Length: 56
Ligand SMILES: [Zn+2]
Image (cartoon, rainbow, N blue to C red; front, side):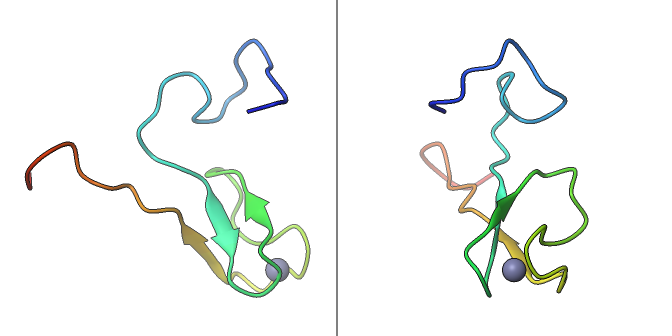
C-alpha cells in the first residue's frame, strides 16, 4: 500500500489473507483487529481471498 512500512505485524509481509472492511463504514481494519476502529460494531468482512487457478 501507499504507506509502505518495512514490515508490520500485518499481512503486508507476504500474506494471501487480505484485510477486513467494515460493512457499516467501509473501514478496513487489520486482520489483527477484532472489530471496526470506526463503529466498533464487530461488522467486518475480510476481502475476497480469491483462488489461484482452481479450487483447493
Ligand atoms: Zn464501522
